[PDB]
Amino acid sequence: FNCLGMSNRDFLEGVSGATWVDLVLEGDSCVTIMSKDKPTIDVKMMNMEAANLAEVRSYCYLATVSDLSTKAACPTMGEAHNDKRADPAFVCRQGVVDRGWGNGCGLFGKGSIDTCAKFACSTKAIGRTILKENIKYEVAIFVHGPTTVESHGNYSTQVGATQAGRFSITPAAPSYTLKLGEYGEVTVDCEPRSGIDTNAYYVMTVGTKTFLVHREWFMDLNLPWSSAGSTVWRNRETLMEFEEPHATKQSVIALGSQEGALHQALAGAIPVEFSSNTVKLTSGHLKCRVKMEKLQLKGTTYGVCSKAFKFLGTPADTGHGTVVLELQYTGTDGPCKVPISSVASLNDLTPVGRLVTVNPFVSVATANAKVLIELEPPFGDSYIVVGRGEQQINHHWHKSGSS
């Protein structure tokens, strides 16, 4: 539910002098928002699904042929009308065959024949549509307040501390406001109409694997099909073979399975997970506005910590040009601001970076409390300084790159 530890991570800045920021979320992506006079927040896309899918059409890729009969007519006796022709489950084909004394007719000539066969589908693939109605996004936001290495990634710890909360976004309710205790609240306005429209591509299940398939490509499939709530097969002759007409018994066969020919035409399509009638989504995004109007820095009257801090290990690169570190405070002088900054030279009285964990606190009055700090040092050499004068500790850092 956080950005710390992830590899897909982006940083954004409140534009100078407003209270809202536009962004574009992504699947399994995390955005960190840094605003002036306001705490830093993480906004992560947790989930995105569509549920209660509607069936559009089904295609048969393996069919059976049974109950073969051919009605025959002698020359001058008209066209043969096989009586199965009115049965909706049967496929019929009219033909013409030579007839004579040798095979049953008193007169010579061409004879009419009508062969029919029952059509049954053994295995089929089901297409289903996603209506923008169905789509749910689930989002999480975390406030960079006082945290610990052990508590920073712990959800119930942060939910209890009123620093994080998960919530969902639908086209029905594309907006939400999360109460963050004494940090105020953050308001999100979202635009859940993106990448996929009311009828854009479909969800096709072929055997055990489910795919997201192009809509026009789906409806053009050269296979027998039936409609949403109807088991009547149309275009069935693509899976059948009527063999050479014979005066008494013309042969009809079904083809072998066409599943290979589907997966062959699905060798690059996007597979998708589809369980308990809901479908998980990996692609796609979500445009939103984040509103930090009522987002407040909390307890900023407190004084700067007086006593000494101690490092609890070598600070570590996050993989995003920032470093993490965890201090420990020997002092007991209540909640106080941690005097931490990133400088170039040791005796410089100015920073050269920016704190990702804006406004660090020790939050308790007891001794030996721990606090996690994230911060962006400049490229090249720098020092991370904590404390003033005799209690001053520092740590040299080097960051690799040019621009």
Image: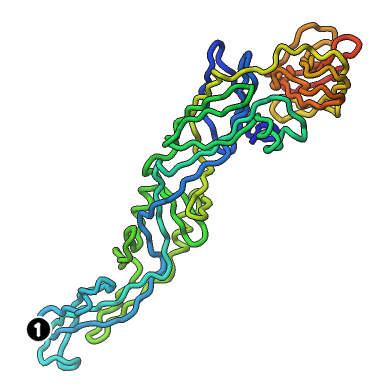
Q: Position of residue 15 (x, y in %)?
A: 55, 15
Residue 308's spot in the image, x, y percent? 88, 17
Left or right placement of residue 44 versus residue 5 in this view: left
Q: Tell me where residue 378 appears, x and y as whole percent.
A: 73, 17
> 169 and 127: which one is in front?
169
Per the image, label 1 sits on a secondary structure element best described as loop
Q: Residue at x 77, y 30 (%)?
A: 148
Instruction: Name the residue rendered at 76%, 7% in the picture.
Output: 350
Closer-to-camera residue (111/83): 83
Residue shown at 69%/24% (left/top)?
145
Image quarter in which the C terminus is found: top right
Q: Tell me if 246 is positioned left or right of 344 in this view.
A: left
Given the image, on which type of amino acid does mark 1 rest? Met
Label 1 CA crowd tier, 10 Å (few <14, some 14–19, many 20+): few
Query: Which of the two residues, 25 or 276, is positioned nearer the viewer here?
Result: 276
What residue is pinned by disc 1?
Answer: 77
From what the image shows, is residue 268 above or below residue 155? below
- Looking at the image, is 159 positioned above or below residue 100? above
- The percent coordinates of residue 103 (x first, y second) are 19, 91
Q: Quadrant of residue 339?
A: top right
